[PDB]
Image (cartoon, coloured by chain):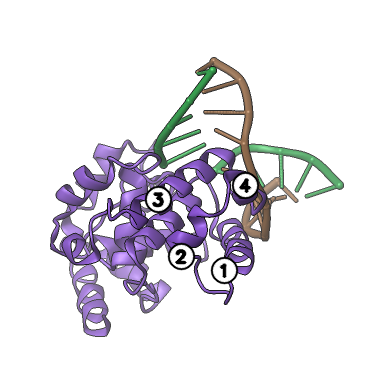
Chain colours: A purple, B green, C brown
Amino acid sequence: KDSDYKRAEKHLSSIDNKWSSLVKKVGPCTLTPHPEHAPYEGIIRAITSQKLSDAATNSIINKFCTQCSDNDEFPTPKQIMETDVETLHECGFSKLKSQEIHIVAEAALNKQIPSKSEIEKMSEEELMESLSKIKGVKRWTIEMYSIFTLGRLDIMPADDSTLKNEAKEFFGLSSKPQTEEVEKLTKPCKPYRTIAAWYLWQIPKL
DNA sequence: GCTACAATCG
DNA sequence: CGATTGGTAGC
């Protein structure tokens, strides 16, 4: 993770030089993934973040953990299953998300979700095909889960709206780029596109 | 003080 | 189509 980042930062400093410049200005990558989280947890966290800022997402999960858990820990599948969507919605989850989160809990409970060991053996394409079967989980959500939970290093969430806004400035484009364009422009960042995305995501903070 | 900012479904 | 969860950065 440490050697991984230093190695990634070096590669990003070895492509064309706007990347070298951004890396130097932003400093060391502080991305902190949580692979210790079970798949159902990582998935629920990713679902919750849809259309919501990290702060908004945090306030919702905090309530969720504070009420639905008996130890401020992340609610277990069983605990979630035994909570109706009405109560989940009161924590701040949209009604739709409440429904999907309940279903994810049921799936985890009934061993319908790939085990973490199997997930770690799946390529991103396989993961996409597998988790996209879950209601409320598609490309973006799986990318976020791969990055923030799994800790994968070569994930380029080219479809991310904020990343597109950043890519427009960074690459000096005349208009917000389409998904395909972002993927093309960041190809040189392989095999550390996750870290490249993170750096782009840090541009606002500058 | 205001208010823009992923995936599903009748 | 037209809704949807909310903290808060940028006005």
For marks 3 and 1, give the CA distance: 17 Å
Q: Secondary structure beneath disc 4?
A: helix
Q: Quadrant of the N terminus of chain A?
A: bottom left
Q: Same chain for marks 4 and 2? A: yes
Question: Circle 3 is placed at which residue position?
Answer: A106
The x and y percentages for residue A99 are 50, 41
Question: Circle 2 is placed at which residue position?
Answer: A76
Report if the CB atoms under discs 1 and 2 are less than 8 Å apart: yes
The x and y percentages for residue A181 are 26, 40
Earlier residue among tags 4 and 3 = 4
The x and y percentages for residue A68 are 59, 63
Q: Chain of mark 3?
A: A
| Disc sitting over residue A89 in the figure | 4
Residue at x-position 22% and y-position 84%: A3
Q: Secondary structure beneath disc 1?
A: loop
Report if the CB atoms under discs 2 and 3 are less than 8 Å apart: no
**Is A64 positioned to the left or the right of A8 in the image?**
right
Earlier residue among tags 4 and 1 = 1
**Is A133 positioned to the left or the right of A206 in the image?**
left
Q: Chain of mark 1?
A: A
Which is more foreground, mark 4 or mark 3? 3
Q: How many marks?
A: 4
Picture layout, residue A63 above or below residue A125: below
Q: Same chain for marks 3 and 1? A: yes
Residue type highlighted by circle 4? His
